[PDB]
Amino acid sequence: PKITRDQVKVPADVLADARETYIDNYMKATQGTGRLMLFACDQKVEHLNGDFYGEGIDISDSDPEHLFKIADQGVCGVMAGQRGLIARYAADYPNVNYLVKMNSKTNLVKTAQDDPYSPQLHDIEAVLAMRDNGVNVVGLGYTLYLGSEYEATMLAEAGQLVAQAHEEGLIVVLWIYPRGKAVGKDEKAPTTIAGAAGVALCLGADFVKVNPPVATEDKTSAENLAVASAAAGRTGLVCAGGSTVEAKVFLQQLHDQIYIGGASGNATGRNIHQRSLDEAVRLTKAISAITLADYDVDRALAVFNGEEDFALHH
Amino acid sequence: PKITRDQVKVPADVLADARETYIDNYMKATQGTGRLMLFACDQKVEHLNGDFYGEGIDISDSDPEHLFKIADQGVCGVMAGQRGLIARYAADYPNVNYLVKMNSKTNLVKTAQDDPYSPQLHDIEAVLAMRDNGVNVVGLGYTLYLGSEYEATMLAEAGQLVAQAHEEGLIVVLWIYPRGKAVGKDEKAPTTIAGAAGVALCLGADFVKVNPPVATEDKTSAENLAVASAAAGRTGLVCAGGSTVEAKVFLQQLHDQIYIGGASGNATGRNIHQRSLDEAVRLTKAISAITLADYDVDRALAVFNGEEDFALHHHH
Amino acid sequence: PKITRDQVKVPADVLADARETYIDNYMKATQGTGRLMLFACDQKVEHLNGDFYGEGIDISDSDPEHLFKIADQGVCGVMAGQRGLIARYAADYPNVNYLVKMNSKTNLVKTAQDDPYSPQLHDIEAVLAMRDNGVNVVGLGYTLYLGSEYEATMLAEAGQLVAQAHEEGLIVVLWIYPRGKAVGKDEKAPTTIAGAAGVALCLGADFVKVNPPVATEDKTSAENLAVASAAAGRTGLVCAGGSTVEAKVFLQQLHDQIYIGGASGNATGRNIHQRSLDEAVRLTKAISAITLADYDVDRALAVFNGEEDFALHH
Amino acid sequence: PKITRDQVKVPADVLADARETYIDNYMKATQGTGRLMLFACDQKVEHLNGDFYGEGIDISDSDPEHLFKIADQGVCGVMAGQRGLIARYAADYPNVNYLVKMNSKTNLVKTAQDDPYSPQLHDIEAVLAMRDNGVNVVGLGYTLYLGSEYEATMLAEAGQLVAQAHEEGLIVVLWIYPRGKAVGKDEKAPTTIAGAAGVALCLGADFVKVNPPVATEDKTSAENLAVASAAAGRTGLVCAGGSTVEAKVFLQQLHDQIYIGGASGNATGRNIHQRSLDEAVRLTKAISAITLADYDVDRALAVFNGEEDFALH
Amino acid sequence: PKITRDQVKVPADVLADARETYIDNYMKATQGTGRLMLFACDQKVEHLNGDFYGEGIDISDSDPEHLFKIADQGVCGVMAGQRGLIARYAADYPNVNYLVKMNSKTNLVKTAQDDPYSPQLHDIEAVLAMRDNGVNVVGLGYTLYLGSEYEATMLAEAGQLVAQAHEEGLIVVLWIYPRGKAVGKDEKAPTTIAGAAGVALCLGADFVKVNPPVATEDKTSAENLAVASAAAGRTGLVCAGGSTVEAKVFLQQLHDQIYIGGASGNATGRNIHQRSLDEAVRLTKAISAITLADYDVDRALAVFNGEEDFALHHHHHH
């Protein structure tokens, strides 16, 4: 798609003096399309070194600079990573739209031992200082585990964060993953994903990242996602394709999520960075072709296979 | 009914420089009647998507803009919702009296697993900033689960919030639902509802939203509510009708709660928004007809059934 | 008794520019006698509606304004109530000495389920703003459950509160009720009450409200209380008479607590407010007669029965 | 012993503008000797009324004013008490060096029920305001229960407290009593006491109060204490003689703690205050004679019996 | 090795007006080499008096001034210790690069009883005040136990600390020891060590201190460490040699860790301070010779044995 500055709907918690900044950031993050292509680079904490070294993982992924190379050479809307990770590389990679992921936890403590809690790692002022030091921070990210016994803590953190972010004209993406004792088998039930989507709207987020819901007898995964996209209202819903599948199967999933599921984009992590730099760059281009330029699966697969190139300036 | 500005009892925690604002907000919230018709739109967190999509729920309710269309085209005192929900739509719906619901939780953790706790989602300054950016925020809302093992945290948050709200001349509605291990079967006992109403006054609330108490051998639900309205003193008690009954039964409950139970208004949520826009608008008009304009049940039912229209009698 | 401004002992934590305000408030609270007659109106939270409606309770008590009428038309030293309760009526009842009860809890969670904790409901600044809006706030109240597993939270709240109160020249009354798993059986042992009294001094309170200790083989309740009054040193101890006894027994209990037990006054709640307005007013006059003006039990009983009037000026 | 202002080692967290104040306070607290005689008056919270009324306790101890009379009439380095207790009496007892005990707990919850936690009762600003109102506050006290499940909370409180106190040129004494599930039988083991003393230094304390360690087969209590005094480095270690025992045995214990155990003084509570005023005052004089003036046990006992007097001049 | 000021990569969270200070501190800490020789003196809290008195520990280690004498007479990059410890001695030992260890806990509560938590002991402002009072504070240290049930608290303290330190131009060393019920036997698995190293980067640390990983069928300890050094990216990884091996084996471990494992330095505590002053000083010199001056194991061992002296080659960092 394509949008103008005037088409950006500025929420009422973005103050008058931050209005233009917010529009700048929304236009950057969505690359002037209204759609969010998110490259997720926050998994060094979440899964430790699991997604970065081992069987089936390209050796270049063992070096963190790999992520910044992909973001710089590939086509993405935003690169989402922890403040410190961005801090150590952004000087050499200034032409990326950075989304600072505000909280993180490891996966060492499993749900069965204790419900998940992912704490805000630092205040917003630390991000603002970095922005004021030349870093192109366009927004913030935060994860909520609804149904966790620690839900309250994350709700309180997330709610305050969205307010402060919009005060500064930063966009906000919430990862909402209902997880815990209470949730169990219902983790990817259609109602759970839809619930998650509605909560992000109520908190004031610009975008919400959810798991794709399971297919039911009644509906496909994408068809169930439509309910969640509706529930999120003026908050854009972004989803994920399976990390395990073929490149064409993956691109088909993303296409369905947008055109049948009503998603406003996607969030892709290990599926990109576990590949060699060349193949990873080609994948981001194929993903962005669907997400930002309305390419059908066939033409996107051509981009991935290197038969065609893709650039935003056309 | 009708009240004038001079009939508004300004409590002593509304400071001199916030007095006129408080009166403005009290008049707006009650539509110049002293009665509170509250349209509850906070349940997207509370019950996730359960109240907004599924069997018996109109397809229009799956879009959250439905709620703002109802508040704007219907007749309500206030629309109560989370800060973020209001933020995303308020610019396109400016002519609504907003009550910002300060806390929320999901219903995923049941009481049997752990006692309930609903945390304040952000500071009051976030709401004030939104107000100063042109949003018609008239007051704040907050839920307390008395008898929860987490009661103390909610008492501390609510107490401070009432003081800060009145400092700014905003009205405060407290939802008080005693819930927990300790409460159980006594959730809707007359003594419990009365206890809840009394606590809200001590915290300094302008209004308290409680469950209707169960009927006993000696007294009806509405008759038992009278004890709670009394306990609340100068804090107005608002109640709710059954979400499950027929429209006439619902409107009778509301009438009885006011005229027998001594309620100063009502809070209605899913009973409104689960209906199509037209029928939802008609229901807000029927409710407001009773609450704001003293309509008989019969005449209110005619508004619900579309036989008569309803608009506000006086504007201030 | 009778005291002058010069006889008021100003503690060292009352700052220089707050000295006169502290003296004003001490003279008001003690009605120029040094003795504290406290009318407790904080039980709408503590016991919910149990103390205000039901059998043996006058129908007028179901309306909260009843409490303010009693305080206005009766004779009291201070009326103790929550900030919010006071806020709703004080404009219509300005000529009362208000003591703002800073913390409260309900009685729904029993000790056997979990140890008690009563949280500070707001900051002191909220009380100060109400004072500066013309409410005659002479002091603050706070409850500590010593021996509770939540003891530490209340000790930290109380200690800070006393310091800030005296900084502003407000008086402080601490309710100290040892309660919890650890206490149980010993709630009203002489040593428990004496311990409670001593702690209030160490926190720096002007007055401490305790339960009366049980009688022992060796000593009467009042005799056991003498040990607690001694332990409290320059902090005045106040106590309560039995809730369910005859008015003459009750007044004899208060007299004993003062003259045998060394109490500096009393705190009475439901015994007063559960009565009809006229009888409630007479009881406050009878209590104040003993506490403030040194009446014997007979003459005070005569005041209760309406054979004699009582007022402070004369 | 005797020290001059120049001999006071000012730690580097005492800021330039607080330097002279710190020296003033160190000289006051140690009475110009470098040794700390601490009179402990904080037990009204710690053990409720148990140390102040009952069998074997003099009747005068039931009135809290007893504590201040002793502090003023006897000879002490500092009087350690809660802020509130000091607030109610200090106006009538201005010539005492006050140490404000910043945290307290009661003894109602035993270790077996739950591990101990003693919370900071108020901010430091509260003490500073009292100081600026003319109260002679020379420093602060704080208790840590290492090995408690609540250890972390007390470490965070104590660490910040030391920094702020030195910023204001106040001295800091830390009570360190390892206590909890994890400690149990090891409460007064030589390694435990030495561990405690080392932690105080790491937090930046000027002095540390510990229990004396038990005797072992190889070493006496006092001999075991030397290890702790060494571990404490430039933090002075103060100890305690056996609670309300014989005056001679008590003074002999304190003497051994200093000259064999390497202690920099003592912290005494109920052994002093549970006595009648006169005898309490004489005991403070006897304790001070050993701690401040290097008296042997025999001459300190003479002071206790009133056969000799003892003063700072 | 040797680096110049221009070769120091200044992260983007070090603000414009803190940049020169940050470089000053990075140059001081690494002695102008880019390598970190860290002398750890924080174990008086961590292990109580266990590392400082007892069998096989020199009697001089029972006096804490021992640590400052070693730091002053030996050759070290930074001396890491608690704020209080540093405060009591720093005036008499001004010519040391101090790293203030921000958190500490005792070892009294074992994992089996409760997962570990080491709390921040005071605010950063306390350290800043000391720096402005003349103490040569070059950086801060903090320990995180990943996989502990208290992981969240430490993540939050550490993240905020890194941001604040860099705002002030201070370097940051994170000790990251995954520890807890959830970790157990996996404490020193190669993947665990690599995970820990990667987290330190994400928080924004300048250096990360980890345990050496165990050897596996496939790889030696040092070969396994290479994966962790890679995961840490632009955060320098520092490791440790065994405390109970012979001096030669110890110095060989450190050498392997650098040249095979990709370490940017080392952290050594009790192996130094449990020795007599003279021997301790000689060991720091041996370690620093490998770490800062690229010595072979054999020539470093000669320094340890007192056959040769060792001093720094370059002092362009004043």
Image (cartoon, coloured by chain):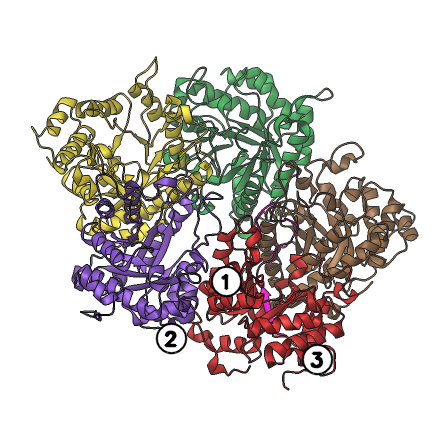
Chain colours: A red, B purple, C yellow, D green, E brown
**Magenta stretch mostly in which secondary structure?**
loop
Say which mark, if any, is on residue B92.
2
Out of E22 and B151, give the one closest to the viewer: B151
- Kindly report the distance in space between the C-alpha atoms of the residues bearing marks 3 and 1: 33 Å
> Looking at numbered disc 1 in the image, what kind of residue is underneath it?
Ala
Q: Residues within 10 Å of mark 2 (few under 14, many from 20)?
A: few
- Chain of the residue under label 3: A
Question: Which mark is in front, 2 or 3?
Answer: 3
Residue at label 1? A194
Q: Secondary structure at mark 3?
A: helix
Range of residues picked out in magenta: A96-117
Question: Which mark is in front, 1 or 2?
Answer: 1
Q: Is residue C34 visible?
A: no
Q: Secondary structure at mark 2?
A: helix
> Looking at numbered disc 3 in the image, what kind of residue is underneath it?
Val
Q: Residues within 10 Å of mark 3 (few under 14, many from 20)?
A: many
Residue at label 3? A303
Left or right of C277 in this view: A179 = right
